Amino acid sequence: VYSYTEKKRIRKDFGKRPQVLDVPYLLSIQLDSFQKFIEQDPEGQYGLEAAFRSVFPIQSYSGNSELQYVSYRLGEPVFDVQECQIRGVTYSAPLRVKLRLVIYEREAPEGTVKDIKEQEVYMGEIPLMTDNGTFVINGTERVIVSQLHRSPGVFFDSDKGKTHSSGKVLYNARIIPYRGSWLDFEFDPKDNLFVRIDRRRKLPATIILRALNYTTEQILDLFFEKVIFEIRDNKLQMELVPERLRGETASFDIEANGKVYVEKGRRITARHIRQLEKDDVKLIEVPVEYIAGKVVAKDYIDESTGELICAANMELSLDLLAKLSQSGHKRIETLFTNDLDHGPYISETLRVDPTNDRLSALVEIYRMMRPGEPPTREAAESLFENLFFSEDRYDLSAVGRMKFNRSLLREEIEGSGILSKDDIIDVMKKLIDIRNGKGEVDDIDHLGNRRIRSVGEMAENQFRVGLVRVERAVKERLSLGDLDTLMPQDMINAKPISAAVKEFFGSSQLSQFMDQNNPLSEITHKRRISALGPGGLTRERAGFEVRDVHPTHYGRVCPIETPEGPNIGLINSLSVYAQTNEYGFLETPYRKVTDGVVTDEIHYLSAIEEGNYVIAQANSNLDEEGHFVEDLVTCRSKGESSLFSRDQVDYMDVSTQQVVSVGASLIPFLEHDDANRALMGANMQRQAVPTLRADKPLVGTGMERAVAVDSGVTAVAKRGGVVQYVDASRIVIKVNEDEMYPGEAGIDIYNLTKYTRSNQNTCINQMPCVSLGEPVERGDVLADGPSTDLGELALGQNMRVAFMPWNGYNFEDSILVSERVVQEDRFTTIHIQELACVSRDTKLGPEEITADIPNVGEAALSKLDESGIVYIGAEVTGGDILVGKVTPKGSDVKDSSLRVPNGVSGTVIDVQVFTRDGVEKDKRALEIEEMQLKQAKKDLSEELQILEAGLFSRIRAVLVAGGVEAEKLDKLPRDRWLELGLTDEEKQNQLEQLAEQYDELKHEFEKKLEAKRRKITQGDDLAPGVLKIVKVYLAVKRRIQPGDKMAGRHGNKGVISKINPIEDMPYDENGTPVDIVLNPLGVPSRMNIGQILETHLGMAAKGIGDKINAMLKQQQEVAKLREFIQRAYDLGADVRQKVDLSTFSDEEVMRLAENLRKGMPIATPVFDGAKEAEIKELLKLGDLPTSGQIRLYDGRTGEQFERPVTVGYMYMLKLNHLVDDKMHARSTGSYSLVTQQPLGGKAQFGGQRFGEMEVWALEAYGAAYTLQEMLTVKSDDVNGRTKMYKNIVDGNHQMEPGMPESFNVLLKEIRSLGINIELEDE
Amino acid sequence: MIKGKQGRFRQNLLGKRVDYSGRSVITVGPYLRLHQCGLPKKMALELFKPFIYGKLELRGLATTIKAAKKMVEREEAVVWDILDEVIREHPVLLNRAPTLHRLGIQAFEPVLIEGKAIQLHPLVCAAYNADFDGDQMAVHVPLTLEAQLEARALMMSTNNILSPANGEPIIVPSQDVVLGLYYMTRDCVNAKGEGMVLTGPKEAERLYRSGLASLHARVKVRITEYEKDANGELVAKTSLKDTTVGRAILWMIVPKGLPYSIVNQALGKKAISKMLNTCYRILGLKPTVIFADQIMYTGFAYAARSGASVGIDDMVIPEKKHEIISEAEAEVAEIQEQFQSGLVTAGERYNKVIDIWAAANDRVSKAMMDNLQTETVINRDGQEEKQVSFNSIYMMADSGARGSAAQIRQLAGMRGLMAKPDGSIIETPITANFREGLNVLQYFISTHGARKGLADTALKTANSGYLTRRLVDVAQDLVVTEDDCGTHEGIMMTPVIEGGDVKEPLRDRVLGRVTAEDVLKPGTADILVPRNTLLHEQWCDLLEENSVDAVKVRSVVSCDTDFGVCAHCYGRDLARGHIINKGEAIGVIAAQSIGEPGTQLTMRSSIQVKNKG
DNA sequence: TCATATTATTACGCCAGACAGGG
DNA sequence: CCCTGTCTGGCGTCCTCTCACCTATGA
RNA sequence: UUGAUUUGGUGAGAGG
Ligand SMILES: [Mg+2]
Ligand SMILES: [Zn+2]
């Protein structure tokens, strides 16, 4: 079964693997994020409720008043989106917050407040999101791009080689909070442990332990295990668990139980450890040279004399043993400092530490953090207890606590946001374990260690900044609060929240201007994952590995769609199937594989879960049950693509598109292209201009439908049904009854956006693709947008291309084009330019909008009214006048009248004017007022009458259970209708019910039309300051010409060189010329062989189209057409499509065959595409030669090209790098102010920067005079250039050079220091 | 305001913005002669406004300057003749935007273009590194009269036919024209007109055009080659060469002095480069300019007549490829069955797997290379006989137009063992080429290997440019300022030998450098060359005949000149045949010639004899 | 409108060059 | 007193094109 | 004596 615009032109779909999961809604990142931001979500997470439950209730410092929260709301926007783009306002909503002030008496923590007050106060306006994922910030339509940043939680990084210049590795460990202070631990090459906070000075790390109220003995209890020396019969024996001897040299005689176990000299092996454990060896008598290097663990004091023997962490000598042995401390605890495993890093750090107690530790930390200003007990304790341990200024989020517990192998995943003692101690323990050998480092490119911020998270963080500023303001006003004479807007202020949130949505590194020239380009700028932005890395610094593709990108980030240039691999684009995790990570779908049978259930994984499992490949042959048909299958285990068994796998890839994105999965035959040319192909495919006549890629991938629907450029039907099709203004859809609400009778009226300006000066235009009285279903398309054709996606157009050298005109990458391409207007794109004119009151009175243009004669008053401003629509070019806008006292009058820029033509399509309340010239301002005034009422009544007509009929329709008397129901016409009483019978309240409808309709229409006139009757609506605001919309129509840039989908760039006549083209023996000749020499080097298979398969597609065009032109009854269409849709191997063609009612075969006579469209999916034998077999169904190559004659000489050439249909696109936006020349005009050199650019009429390497190139020749005029006369020296212009126009090519002006600018800037630079003797 | 990249030195005093300048997208226009370029009419009327004003005021059509500015603002019918009379002999400086060496600013004569795109002669593109994928160039106008003469006499595009970094010609025919020549001068074992005899090259082209022979059909012709064996006198020798039809047609374009054996071979790209080089060394500059143009015209014309496409059938899969892959799969199966039983170590396993996949890769490449280089087997009057193939991708590879062994290898044979960004190789290769489909994992490993290359170029270019900057600012001063420093010291140029076969011969190192003391002939105490002779090609051939050991030659670092380098201790001019002139800045051309290849460079037991002596 | 005058983030990679520390 | 980690400064590609956004305060 | 403001500076994106 198919929908009704699916039976229009059903694309022949190759593809063997049955898809199990359909493509998700391609704009779901932006929409789900911002729907999380604004939503009334009780339990607080996440959203605006999290912000209000963090900041509220505010209580002041015992001020006995506590403003609390109830509920918030967003009212209607005062401007809908279209008039918002027209006017220039933000597309925002007012944020109505209920606030409840309660005020206490004296001594009321528990006492009832003395008075309350509560109001729906107004703070800020937040910009809402349009239904397509965009904002409208100041008239322009912008997009917030999702950031990719390091997750909160600990990271164990190495930096193995570069420091110390000695090959000794370090190991640092960064505890990155979501909000607050950064804490880093790091080794130094003396093997000492150092802490630093916020990249400040370096403190030896155990001072932070001494800041957490840990004595030295507790620290040594933590990071070291005790070795027990017992004072015994002789020589102070040792408890020896045999694990501690692993891998060391036996220094002494190892004997016990009257038996010599291990002698001196040999290293202790694990067999000797087994001997000591089997022989149960713990207590052995040591020599005195064994204890002479060890370190004591805890303190010991001489008991009778009452003083200290040794401090903790003290190495032992023999006389120290003579001190402690004679006192009476029988147990001696020593620190086991294994040189292999258990290193003495904490102990040597304690030897570096200049502190001894907690208080001096806090004083040293306070002298680190805030220097100069003294370190007192209260100040240092408040500093350190609010560094990490308070809920205000340090907060690992839920993501941070999950990563923090996961990297430390904790059991739980939810905990408190602040740190604790045990967390810092665990980070130090894991860092020490990594130094010892056990456990390993983390990498930073691993996408399980890399979170995504999106629109709702970033706007929530900015909103929380605004709320903490307004709570500091509320704490300010409340302690100065006098009661009861204030209500909660003398306390609260709508200014900082609105200021912060407009600061982010206006001027941020991620709220950026939408690339809008293409449905693809909109939908792939909204799905963008940037590494840049605040808190992330920069373009000009880093690096090599963060610009590179890591094995966790499989199915999360597109490997091949990243922009080439200064930021490669920072501006990654998101994959097709990849959602976003609850915590913000990238989870991608996989198919759960319990046993041999691959189950059709899906299950989402992130990269910290994808490593543990074994995940199969998308294309591994499985037949009829899910069993892998091989006994071994390529999978990947832990980022390593390897071959595993038939029955080990736990997951399989869902579909074979899932590695790449929606820009580079529209490229058919992707798997045959090179990676570089697929990158260049996707990046150019974003840049296509919408042509005037949209044309359906013959070789597509089938993802055109999802991109053209999911990007909101087409008018997808909301509720299904039929159609009324007024359409000149709007599509009117009558709704079928099942999808139709009981009240609100209701028919859907779709607004078509006709010719208007895009963000890239292209033309966004919608055209209805459904006729009158034609069924449509829910989700079906109704109006084709820019670059769409019946709901598909038509960026460029499909043309007949020959691969051959043709007389040098396609030399390096150039492209030689027939005249049949430029006669048919099949690339003639439409550009629209907005031009503003304002008459601001700079000085010496205000400027004026009058035709009475001066000095200039009857060459001003022409394309305008009898007395001012461009009329409506003519063929204006360059140097014309659009808006007469000149002042007197500015003879002394002048010409600021905004004219048409140099080189452009066009038609004035629209003139907008919300000017300084007064613009009316003669009486036009109020003349149109009456026109709109009468317009509103007309439609208002019309619509009511339209429904009235439907209701009147409905009244009679229902009039059967309570008066069906046809001759007794046609009484009053426009007066009443029902003069009976149904009462009950079988409930037809229905008459009374419909009576209310009409009664309310007229009653509401009056009020509806009442406000209409009110709105109509007005000067105009805009902001203040600016006075004369005239915007004129030109529309140039640019065709194609030698110098434009065209390109296919594979990376084959080209500058169209010669626009040949039709005759000189290479025609085949049938007679048709070829349209575009490309060059075969690009194909062996640039290894993008997919354009040839697209060429052959498009040739086969148009072969079927020519065959259907013959069978339908030379008209046959529909049996032969349905037989040939059925053969065309069966065609070859096992596919997914076949068709159910004998259910197309003998007319839907014919409408399909009317839409196929330009070529049968073929879906070649991304990595499961059409094989070559099917291309040959499809070329045999059409009557074309199997090789794909036709013999071609030459249009010049009439004689055959030897060795037959390739002709086919490639889908070639016109990129928006047009040659009459690049052509520029300058002889003489205006310059800058500071310098005497020419200005730069094209919009400024400026000259070429003759840069540094060109000066070196002229020095490389003997061009001393060419360089002398190149930097003195042509550029800078003012006397030289005026003398040169007069010398040229006299006929004397001679320069009088002088000295450059910018060098005298250099002399004054150097001399304006204390520097006396001069110019010496003659 | 002083320091930095955007101070006054680097932004307003060393580089300035410039009037009488323009900029637009380039395109080909192959009808041009190589001293002229196409320049649009709109840019031409804007760049030449004062010359047109002066011309209009000379005729007497107008009076005041205003009238002339209204005339060209309206663009009447008479200013286009004025424009063709200000263009005619007035060169312009075309400039591609990343100018690295001095061949990136060249002066042309304009030919006016209906259009908006600069038409640029194709051979000159290999100097600018200019393809036509969206490139842009700037035009500058030499205003004064000394600058017009410097554009014609120093910077003209006919004057830059040798790269200043070496002796190699920079107007080498790039890509379409070598395919047209390689298809033209070739042969096949049977065609129309096999083994017929022709009375000249004129009727060879007449037999090709009328339709009685083929472009490659072996034939005895009678050609008259002019060998100039006397002292400046050209002696005619006429003979019958067993050659083809295409070699005679290409002999109609060769100038007089070159011998016929320069076209008798198959003419790839190295052969056409040494054809233009021998023409420049023998017949000088003007026949080499006109012969470079005739090469380009006949290459484009017969490449158009060739119809040399590319198809899907042209990439011939080896029939032996699948059995090679199965033998490699059996070998990795044996190694992993030893790995389950623990007989071998892990590093030796990884080394054995990379070794057998390298061996299988080389065998697949040899299978496809035999299957492409001699696939054509056509009979002539009897049994079969084999020849080199006319496969399209093989002519695009063998001609040296575009393609190598590696790229044609990746389109037919397996595309090797791609490496992960860890730097170590991956033990499971990409056994599928591009004609067969890559599946998902193989394309992802390919994207590892290609993202690393794009990141390397886009970060390598900054270090390459900063290296050229440091080099031209250490050089910056050094000007050829004498004619002889009057010394006897100079470095000892030997051929360099690393331990393999002799890498760079002495004729590459002592070509065009003036000897320090007089080289003794290797026999005994003979004055073979004198002590201040420039060693051009004739002297270097008389050095190679006598097998001279090593030459003590004068080097720039031994020059005794205070504040500059004398004219003998530099050497040959390198883009001029003679010695360096008194004046020509050699520090800047040297710094550009070292730093300009900075892009092509990368960024990131006992002795066994080989020969017998 | 017309004088008043500066604070609560961190996440480059060498590579010279100068400086306090210690055998 | 001669090595020495450690800290501080100083580099990091040219040319071009499009768009938007610009200090608070205040009797 | 017959006319006028971007360069300044930031941010974002793009081409070769
Ligand atoms: Mg290019
Ligand atoms: Zn010298």
Image (cartoon, coloured by chain):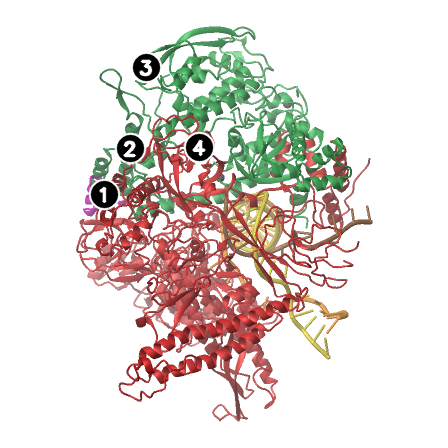
Chain colours: A red, B green, C orange, D yellow, E brown
Q: Nearer the viewer, mark 2 or mark 1?
A: 2
The image quadrant of residue A1196 is top left
Q: CA distance from mark 2 to mark 3?
A: 29 Å
Q: CA distance from mark 2 to mark 1?
A: 39 Å
Q: Which residue is mark 3?
A: B194
Q: Amino acid at mark 2?
A: Val
Above or below, A897 relative to A993:
above
Q: Amino acid at mark 4?
A: Glu
**Helix, strand or loop at disc 1?**
loop
The image quadrant of residue B330 is top left
Mark 3 vs mark 4: tell me if same chain: no
Q: Which mark is residue B316?
A: 2
User: Magenta segment range?
Assistant: B330-346
Asked if labels 4 and 2 touch by Cβ distance under 8 angstroms, the answer is no
Q: Which residue is mark 4?
A: A1063
Secondary structure mostly taken by the magenta-highlighted segment of the chain: helix
Question: Looking at the image, which is closer to me, B291 or A931?
Answer: A931
Image x and y of residue A362, in percent: 52, 71
Question: Looking at the image, which is closer to me, B14 or B437?
Answer: B437
**Helix, strand or loop at disc 4?**
loop
Disc 4 crowd rating (10 Å Cα; few below 14, some 14-19, many 20+) is few
Q: Amino acid at mark 1?
A: Val
Image x and y of residue B266, in percent: 39, 20
Q: Which mark is residue B344?
A: 1
Q: CA distance from mark 4 to mark 1?
A: 72 Å
Q: Nearer the viewer, mark 3 or mark 4?
A: 4
Q: Nearer the viewer, mark 2 or mark 3?
A: 3
The image quadrant of residue A990 is bottom left
Above or below, A1109 relative to A1198:
below
Question: Looking at the image, which is closer to me, B412 or B428?
Answer: B412
- Using the rendered image of the protein, determine whether residue A442 is visible from the camera's viewpoint: no
